[PDB]
Amino acid sequence: ESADLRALAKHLYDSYIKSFPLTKAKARAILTGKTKSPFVIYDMNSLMMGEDKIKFSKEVAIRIFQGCQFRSVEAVQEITEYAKSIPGFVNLDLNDQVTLLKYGVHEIIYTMLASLMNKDGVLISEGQGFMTREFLKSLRKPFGDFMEPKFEFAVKFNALELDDSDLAIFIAVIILSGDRPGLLNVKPIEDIQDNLLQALELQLKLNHPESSQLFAKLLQKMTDLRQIVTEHVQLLQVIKKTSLHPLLQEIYKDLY
Ligand SMILES: C=CCc1ccc(O)c(-c2cc(CC=C)ccc2O)c1
Ligand SMILES: C=CCc1ccc(O)c(-c2cc(CC=C)ccc2O)c1
Image (cartoon, rainbow, N blue to C red):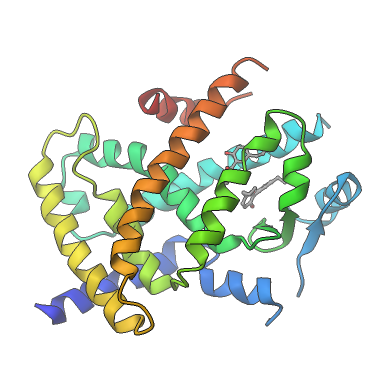
C-alpha cells in the first residue's frame, strides 16, 4: 500500500521536473544568492533597461499586463502536459480532462508562482529578472492591484517550506477535484484524488518531521486558492472597462 504511494510520488516528481522550466529548488537558490544574478526591476528606468537586457512600445502598465498574460498562457500549456502524466488522467473522458484543466489551471499557476516569490518581489523570464513587489503596486489603477493578493498568499504559503516533491503531489490533488462544475464522471476522478491525497499525506509525514499540521494546512490552502482566482477574475472584469487573450477569455467565462 505504502510502496505504491511512494512510487506514485516519484512518478509525479519526475514528470514535474520535465513539465516545468523553473523548479522551486532552482528558484530559491537564485533568490538566496546561492548560485548569475537576475536583473532587478524596481522602477520605471530599470523596467526599460530590463526589457532591453533580458531575453523575453505601449503604456508601461499595459506592457507588463500583456507579458504576464502571455506567460499565463504558456503556464497552462505546461500544466496541461503535467496533468496528462498523472496516472489515470488520460483515461478520463476528454470533456472532463478539459473541464478539470479549465477550472484548475489558475489555482496551479498561483501555487507555483509562490516558488518564484519572496517578500520583496518575483522572479521573471525563467529567473533572468526580478520584479519588485512595490514596483508592481505602483502601477496605475487597477493594474497595481493584480499581484498583491498573490504576494500575500505566497509569503504565507512559502512559510510552509514545501519542496518540489511535495508540490508535485499537491498540484495533482488540485487538478483532480471531483466537485468542478459540468463534470460527466465524478467517481473515477474522486478515486484518483483519494489515492493522490494518501500519497500526499505519506509524503508530508516522511519529508516534514518538523510539523504534523502540514496536511491539514495544505487542505486549507486549496480553498484559499479558489478565493484568489475569484478575486483575479473580478479584477479582470473591471479591465473590460479600460488586448485580452482569447484562450484566457474562454477559461474566464466558465469562472464567472
Ligand atoms: C506565471 C504566470 C504569469 C502570471 C501569474 C500571475 C499573475 O497574476 C499574472 C498576471 C499579472 C498581471 C499584472 C501585470 C500588470 C496581470 C495579469 C496577469 O495574468 C501573470
Ligand atoms: C515586463 C515584464 C513582464 C513579463 C514578461 C514576460 C514574462 O514571462 C513575465 C513573467 C511574469 C510572471 C508573473 C509575475 C508578475 C512570472 C514569470 C514571468 O516570466 C513578465
